Image 1 (tube, rainbow, N blue to C red):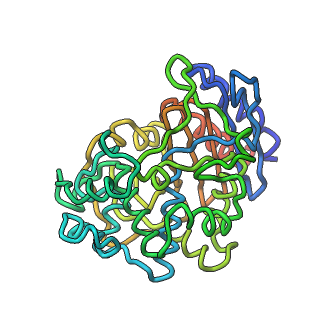
Image 2: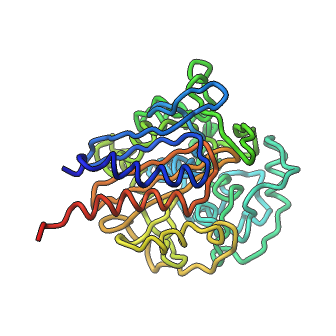
Length: 367
C-alpha cells in the first residue's frame, strides 16, 4: 500500500524542483521495508542524450564522507586507532606540529580549530605538499570548541585511518570497504569499463564539469556511484547487523552523536535530527551558514546512539553535481536523491521531505 502512491509522490516532490533549478538529470532510490523503488528523471548527458537510470554514476561529493567514516569505523573496531588518539600518532611526519594536540575525533567532526572548508589553491595532490600544509598550519580556534565544516579536516581523518590500517586509503576503499558493503558500482576512480555510465555534471550556463584531482579528494568527496548502489549503502546503514560482524560494528561507529549545533547532532560523516522535525528546521540544519560559518558546539556528556526516532542525512556536492541521502532507522526508510547539477541544499531537502512526509501521512488510521 505505501508503494501504491509512491510514483505520484516522488514525481510531485522532484519535477517542480528540477524545473525551478534547471536540473538536467536526477535519480531517486527509496528503500521501503527493504524493498527498493527507483525513479529516474531526465538526462545523464545533454550532449549525448543518454537518459538517467538507476545505474547512472553520479559524483556524490561530500556524501563520500560517510564512506570515509565507515573505513574509520573499521579501523576503530579493529583497535588500530581510537577517537582520542592524537593525530600525529598515526603520521610521524606530523609530530611536533599542532596535530600533536588535535584528536582524531576533532578531525572527523570539523572541530580541530578552523581547518578551512577547502585546502588552499596552492596545495596540489601530492603527499609532501599535504604534509607540509598540516605541519605549518596554525589554528583559528581552540580544538573542540567550534565546528567549521572542512575537507582538510575529515580528509586527514580518513588518511590517518588508512595509515592506522597500514594501507593507502584508495586501496582500502576499493579492495575492502566497497566489497564488504556489496557495492560493485561505486568507484573513487571510474574504471574504463564503466565510463559510459558516468553522467556529465552541469554548472552555471550548463558548463559540463566532472571533478578534477585534488589533495585528499578520495577521502572528502571522491565517490562516484549509482542511485541503486548508494541505496544499498543506505540499506546497510539501516541494518548493519545483516553484515559480517567487523563491518556491522564499523557502520555502528558512524551512528554515534558527539555534540549538537542547533537541531543537528554530529556523527562520523552522518548528521542527525530528531524525527519528526519541521521542513524548515531540517533545511536550516542543511543551510549554507551551517556549512560555511563557524558554530559553537553543545558537547554531549556521552556519545549518543543515533537510532530510533531520528533522521540521519548527508548532503554532498561537486562543481557539477548535488547529492542527498537520508534514512530513518525507526521507519525503516531510506532515500537517495542524485542530480547532475549542484542545486541548493534547501531544494534537496524539499524533495526528501515531501517523500518522507508523504510516506508518513500514509500511515494513519482512516477516521
